[PDB]
Image 1 (cartoon, rainbow, N blue to C red):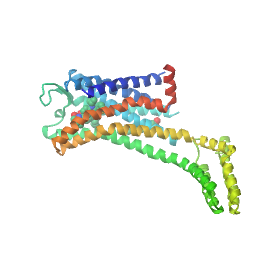
Image 2: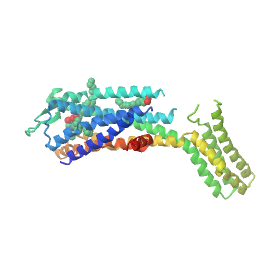
Image 3: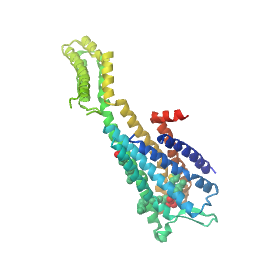
Image 4: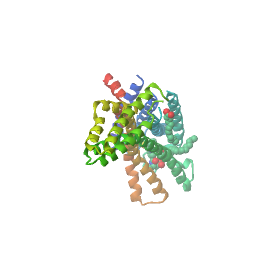
Length: 381
Ligand SMILES: CCC(CC)n1c(Cc2cccs2)nc2cc(C(=O)N[C@H](CC(=O)O)CC(C)C)ccc21
Ligand SMILES: CCCCCCCC/C=C\CCCCCCCC(=O)O
């Protein structure tokens, strides 16, 4: 009685939200993944009224064996396709941070592959799903029959075999790829920011310093950070007109640090602090804006943020489903008490709601991070 309501709520939110996303993308490099996610999320929730009616009828499937096989199959392919599309979107956001449109062709290929690979991994569910009176309650259930692939003493090896494969490909491998993407990109972004943090932190140190040696020490660390940010090539590729302007901006800053460094060496603390404060002028403020703009700093921070929200929304939504399926896999295999077997069984339909929550949450995360979808939806509003 509780679960059917949630299944209905996610059905409306899922098809209206992801329906609005497809309307927009059909009215960039990572835009293949967006439209694939919209159509995977859309097929994922589309047969839920069948399972909402099934759960309401105290687990009694009235729609026959073909709708039991087809409904489960469409859900299971959407299940993998949307995970693989989230992982492909997280990998495309990773490349937009490291590398500098051939990706428009490549993304289409990647999406095509994961769409076939998903429709093939979901094939065992299309095969073993069947309807019959399981555990004799007089109501027919839509269950996965492992008896058509093994004897009584072997149904576990199939249940575990397919179950472990489902979690490995549907959770462990994509989360391992999305975490690797985060760890590499976060490192790269935290390289540019480290040099700019060092510059600002040490300027505060010069302002409050009490002697020339303290001012000299902070200037030395600022000078090494300025040259460190000059060596890191921005997202532009020899001695081109635009390339010289980047290095000249840094040369002004390094020169001003050297000017204060020579005053510090002569023991002129007040004059060195005043010389250091030249970096705060409007002239040097636009040099900072030009150089931080040339590096694509705020634009790469937004890109890293996109990865984190994908990784986390996914880890939070799918962990309960994958933890309880893996725990139940072991409860039946290495036998656990019926107190714990029956717990995992009854908490499992709640795990499918929190996992479904990912599908209808996505249209809002696109609306958050992409102001082009915000402007495409607000024009139609
Ligand atoms: C296709 C139907 C949907 C439900 C709408 N469904 C999904 C995909 C999703 C739909 C919505 C969110 S996830 N996965 C499922 C996994 C099982 C399952 O493994 N049951 C185990 C016994 C067995 O092996 O048959 C026992 C539990 C206690 C572990 C059952 C239904 C599953
Ligand atoms: C050519 C066929 C492809 C080979 C498949 C190998 C990978 C199998 C992995 C997942 C298949 C789905 C298994 C689902 C686990 C049981 C969940 C359920 O009760 O529906």
